[PDB]
Length: 112
Image (cartoon, rainbow, N blue to C red):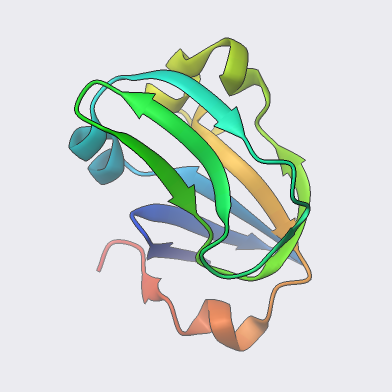
């Protein structure tokens, strides 16, 4: 199941929630040239996940969900090109567990 929040894609697969870039966010910030993750494994809503420098702005990716970080796309720090891609294996940011079902359900559906 796919949701959108904070211009991020959130996909539920079993107990794991993958948070990725969207084309809308890419278009709004421009080309990413730098990407640095925070080291907090227990996120609250609005906690910083990832700091970006891009051609139109710098910004922070803020978590739309409380949860526990199980995977970060640390490849993007070496190769920020990945986060400008359309490919799901390249443009993901983090995977969370220990997410509240109702809080995910309350997000807007991806597409509309």
